[PDB]
Length: 196
DNA sequence: CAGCTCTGTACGTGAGCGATGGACAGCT
DNA sequence: AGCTGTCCATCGCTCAGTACAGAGCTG
Image 1 (spheres, rainbow, N blue to C red):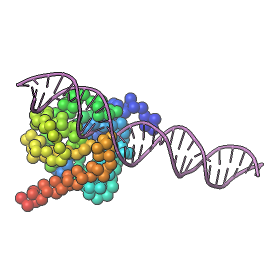
Image 2 (image 1 turned 180 degrees about the vertical axis):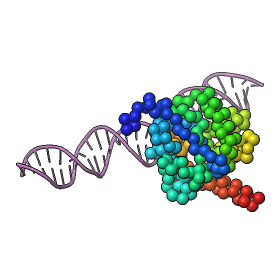
Image 3 (image 1 turned 90 degrees about the vertical axis):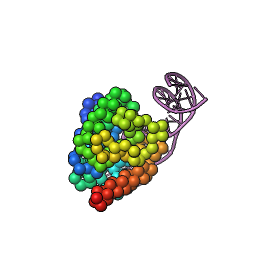
Image 4 (image 1 turned 90 degrees about the horizontal axis):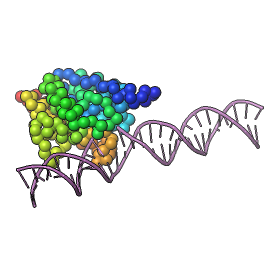
């Protein structure tokens, strides 16, 4: 990576971008190498996140990973990951690392209490659900889940990973439906709060 | 049996690498 | 004209979770 070794990148981490009073926290899996290199969320040339964010109207202009620190204040959106350690991929992580992450994540969510905890990936919600809700359904679906983060009113919302690795949702366009329904959920919640 | 859970196989786009070679201008 | 190197268009290529079948487990 412009002369930086993988071995160097494996030891970097990616800072969370979290505040109080967020509408949404995007929870990725763990930093990939490019994220680790950049120190910003979803820089992957092919990752669909920033494209989907704009295509859905969650951002009114096309943003990119360099804009990530502006999202809390301007857009009501923050970032963390289920697991902190950088790896060359999401099947390099152990079940223990995942469960440790889940525990850490739920404490972060109990602290910051966003309106909506967004799992950027079905696989990490599968883990979270088992660990936190003691529930594994056989037919986990995308979208809104039926359990709030414990001791909070923060909902859980699941999307197909923005990584372009998965073939079932081959393009940004194939995932945008979930970002639109995420926008609608936020808008609904704000509307309830506004109208009491 | 019937539900699990656990493991390994199989899958579509598009961005951007290095390699290649065509267009072209400088120089003789 | 003949030679040569640069630029750049273009290529083939790689590669950034999910669904599901089947084996194993257990009630």
